[PDB]
Image (cartoon, rainbow over all chains, first blue to last red; front, side, top):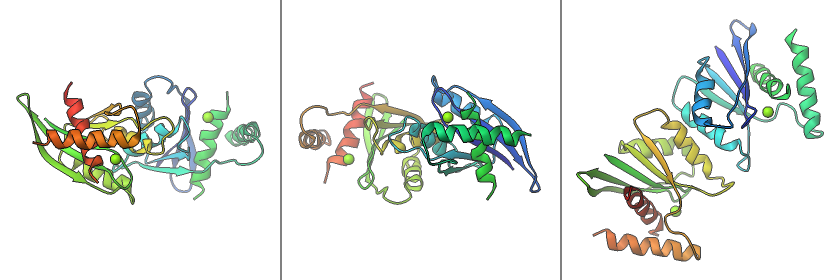
Amino acid sequence: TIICSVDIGIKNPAYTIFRYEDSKVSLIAIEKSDWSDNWEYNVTKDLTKYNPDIIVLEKQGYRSPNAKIIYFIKGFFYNTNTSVIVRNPTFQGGSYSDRKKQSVITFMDKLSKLDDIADSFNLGIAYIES
Amino acid sequence: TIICSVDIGIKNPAYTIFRYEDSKVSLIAIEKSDWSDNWEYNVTKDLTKYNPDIIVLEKQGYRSPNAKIIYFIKGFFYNTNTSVIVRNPTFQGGSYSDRKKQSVITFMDKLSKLDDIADSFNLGIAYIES
Ligand SMILES: [Mg+2]
Ligand SMILES: [Mg+2]
């Protein structure tokens, strides 16, 4: 099963591709992108590039400029082999920059503008552990 | 070509189906629905029911929680033989009451609570003037 956990953003989107076979997780790819222009074309292209079995997203809120993107993805993959799972922020508390720092920290510690890739990565891990 | 102009709503979604052959428009159906529960399920079921070639919707306004339905539809019909057009409100200006009232009135004359079906009706007609 191929997991595509993405950290939704307009100009700063990012997603990490994992492979989960036999309780053995493996980082297949990591990529930054740009959905500031022609988001619809790029959103489908980027998320279908690796044919994920599961796409993980973070809850956005109707007042967010990212909300349109989360609902497009749900509709696009609705009734297909890919299942879209939406979660809550991996990190919560302190200030905005506080969560963005421990996210990047946790990220580089696990490998062995980074906050977008860090988030996407950490989001997949938080999901996989379930 | 089958055109499905929809008047998005949670409890009062309505949509009219127009056939358009030889520069001759004709009513095929007019339906009220309910998207209070499992809107994803009902939205897809209702809009594909009459196999439209085009879906016409109207902008829901900045930071509107019902925009989720608009993007879900764009994403669902993305890259299929179904075009999704989003138009601006058909009746603008004045009070909400007058806009609904002008829709119902206008809808009653051309046809030869009713604001949802009329709104959806007038939306299709407006799109056709294109
Ligand atoms: Mg980000
Ligand atoms: Mg209505």
